[PDB]
Amino acid sequence: RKEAERIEQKLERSEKEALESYKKDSVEISKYSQTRNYFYDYQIEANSREKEYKELRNAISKNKIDKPMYVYYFESPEKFAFNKVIRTENQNEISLEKFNEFKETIQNKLFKQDGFKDISLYEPGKGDEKPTPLLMHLKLPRNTGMLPYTNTVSTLIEQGYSIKIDKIVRIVIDGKHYIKAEASVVSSLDFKDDVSKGDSWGKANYNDWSNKLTPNELADVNDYMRGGYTAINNYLISNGPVNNPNPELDSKITNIENALKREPIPTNLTVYRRSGPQEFGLTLTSPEYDFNKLENIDAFKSKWEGQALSYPNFISTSIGSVNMSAFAKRKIVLRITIPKGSPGAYLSAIPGYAGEYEVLLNHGSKFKINKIDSYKDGTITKLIVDATLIP
Image 1 (tube, rainbow, N blue to C red):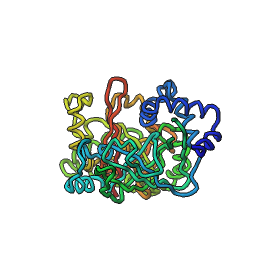
Image 2 (cartoon, helix red, strand yellow; image 1 turned 90 degrees about the horizontal axis):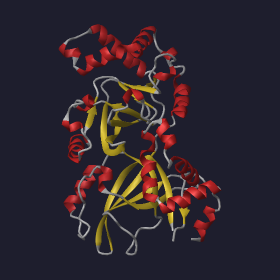
Image 3 (cartoon, rainbow, N blue to C red; image 1 turned 135 degrees about the vertical axis):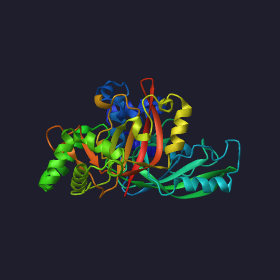
């Protein structure tokens, strides 16, 4: 505990203040840290928990590990899209069938992790709170912020990365079976609500992009951004190249694709799209689109989690996660990890009518849906779809 006393002395008074509050209200504060960035900028600024979020975020950055460190924490199976129990809480055994099913569910997938989390440095034993049958054993990389603190002793981190589960093992603690998931961190540039910082990145990486394009490519990209996108994307969505061929539109599509391949996304990058229901085969009047009903979330997850979402059209995204007037009522936030080397361009590097903080992805792109979350925006449940662009 005297070790935790050391690190607390390193904190500013305002950070100590945020930590005192965290000790009293950890659940709500951690919940806020997960979804804060999905609201309007003015909503973020207005929230009573925002100032303390920033202070506590700063506090954790005051102690960065010098070498990688393994940590333990319990997690719900639902966190990795296993939407059923591994075993009940009064059961001791986990069946081998269930073990294999969970392995099949999690393999070859990256999962976005966000928000404040309490962890332990030691494997939980008999005298520890073990609320689920799933124990994460995660390797945190060098320079990860870590805040040990006393309450009556724990360690606080802020998750801002993706994890992959490399191996699962069935272990026994106090006569009970648990799945222990050995996991690794995969990084991705993620601006979340900091659109200004994302814009600085976008401009730095794409200011010179227009000048790398041929006259035909430039003209077709300009025409797309000026409003041609509607005709082009509707054509692609309806399978026009087959059903009602337009070779003029086809040539534009070819040029825009080649433009997006000209300077590939230079690093793993997270982007955000507010999707309309049509992108998932629904309409505004679809009863299934009412995510305030749990059965509709259940049905949506069953259809889409673990499956590929395909876009015949070009995909407009933003480096910012914030809500915006243009898509205020859209209920589905597609949160996409773009692997380094993927086609794409920051279009808002061209001054004019460029969309807001816009990154355009190539037509025909496929997105693997890893996990679906929900949150309340006012009284309306909205979804966050954790997806990876498939090469």
